[PDB]
Length: 152
Length: 348
Length: 127
Ligand SMILES: Nc1ncnc2c1ncn2[C@@H]1O[C@H](COP(=O)(O)OP(=O)(O)O)[C@@H](O)[C@H]1O
Ligand SMILES: Nc1ncnc2c1ncn2[C@@H]1O[C@H](COP(=O)(O)OP(=O)(O)O)[C@@H](O)[C@H]1O
Image 1 (cartoon, each protein chain N blue to C red):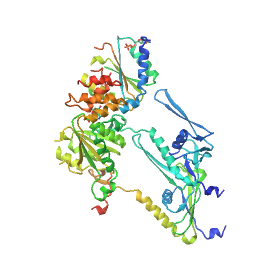
Image 2 (cartoon, each protein chain N blue to C red):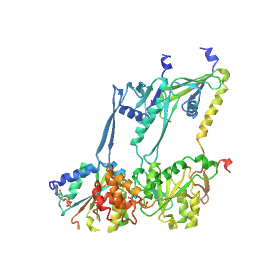
Image 3 (cartoon, helix red, strand yellow):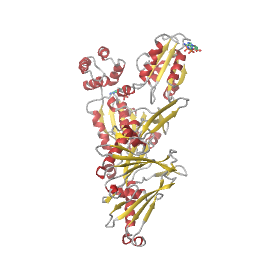
């Protein structure tokens, strides 16, 4: 056991961190892996009307999987706690554990960077335009969209 | 144990997800299964009165069942936690686990899609109509119902010439963004009064489940009204031929949002605005056609083809301003009786 | 207690009108219906309407006979209600017909009407 823990690294991403959903989203879209388990995640928006916009997507889910990032054979576990309950999302406390050799520790940042990009590609800002209303600045013209510099 | 976990998949739907009730509802209505266990689910609404509307329905419930979807023999367990308590619904934490072979993993999405449809069939939207109250939009006329596009009957090609132009305009976000032009579009339904324009706009908004922020024709607040529109809306401008004109064009060019901004315009007689970016799709919905009269007659009375022709050649004579509102009026007063309509509508 | 056939001629017309949602939706006509109980004063009309509302456990939004707010009153009715118009023979008439044609809701909209002497409104969609 000590020799095995002496040639590997770990990386725990716990369910509180913002980099938990990002990483599962990334690992869903990875081409080469073997993930026997799956978990549904369904977003579901009810507007002012009874109208519903809903969408479901599968993710790795509890139990361990494997992945091959750049010739690494990373082993990932995902675990749920049988006793503790988070109050931020109303779900039990979860934990993802990545594990590769020590030699490829430098891969982890790369992975997380990729995840951040796949996270940042979807979330898009909107350039709010404030304006003068007497001696105080008020918002005006509910958020515009980015004008995408090649366009000008 | 490792070989067995080596030829199967799992799918955990946990009790927090919205796709938990949907799936149990779906599996209740599946024809071929063997579910020894059952659980009651009782909805119970007490109104302002002591009156009660209550309804109970059985679902799979705890313990494992079986099902056969498309020749798969899926095994499903449902479990409750003896220690944890959810605070959203006040119940212990539950979990559904589907398990089939790896080869039929692609079935899961299908199942969930079916569940979503059985979920989406019951929940029905209602096209709220906002309106102008000074320089601010207030709700008006507590939610209507969807008008169900087959119900409105207009000319042969106009029902598809707009339902596909709009469906294209909902897919050209990148095209409008990369060119550096605003992402908006106008429409000009024109014709005689009482031809079914507003009815068609409401039917289309019900198709796209948006909300009609109706506005009929002050110039300083018109710009404020254009700029401040709620989420998921479809602007409607009745009678644009009643007008400040330069301010109208200025505010009409200065309409923006964070998403699509469709702005239909209806007028009774359309005689600079027709430039693209402003009004760019003009189509003429007018009086009744021998196709419209046939389709209305078949809309009211399903089947009974023989009478249909016998009406059309009758309405070919004595017709001046025959409009579809008039046909709706003269067909609703003689409901469930086409033979009375044959002699009643022909004389008006 | 009223005449021999009238207790069933209305308790089955209403029970049909509660089952024709698809029929009224597919035709593209609004899903409403009026009624005209007429007779001499003191015959038991209002009592029958209250008994029927108790049968369907709805709520009687009674209104007895201003034209600009009448439309607002017609439009804004609570959930699970049954409109009642006492003495429609006391009237603005064009505004009455306009607001009466412009009554809407998210569900059924029954509107009984009682009058002591009923002498255009009788067209279907209206009474
Ligand atoms: N093609 C149609 N199908 C169904 N109802 C129609 C049709 N054309 C007109 N109507 C009816 O005519 C009435 C008034 O027409 P409306 O659409 O309000 O007129 P406009 O749009 O010209 O102002 C409504 O009750 C509407 O349902
Ligand atoms: N068949 C009946 N059953 C019960 N009460 C009745 C009946 N007929 C008349 N009444 C009595 O008539 C009275 C007045 O009825 P009301 O509804 O005010 O009459 P109207 O609708 O003609 O104005 C009530 O006190 C009611 O109990």
